[PDB]
Length: 100
DNA sequence: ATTATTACC
Image (cartoon, rainbow, N blue to C red; front, top):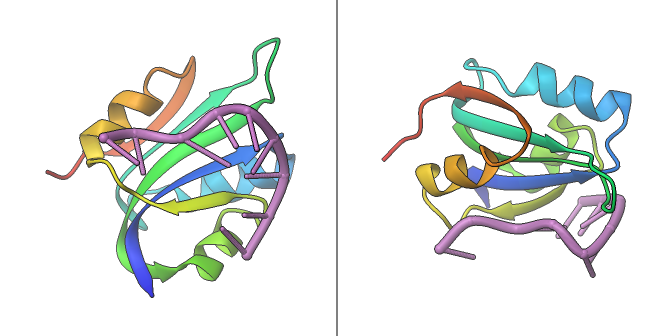
């Protein structure tokens, strides 16, 4: 039950949430990663992203890697589907290139 | 696992 391709959301992200995302979402760990940040007026601020990991991870392990407050789900769309969705966010961090 | 109603297809 360990997988490479995941989506995640971190609602009301904390300092440590950002620190975990910044250290983990790197080319060392990911073939491709994209993480958007939205914190506008009438909604809960979030980090929201997609990870195509180099190594399989069990959900409990990825949860720890992302700071322990993340919602996780096995990715259902393609890397490019996720790139297009997350790149709509007003700020985003993009690591690597989508795999097809 | 986990905070939320946001979350790819």
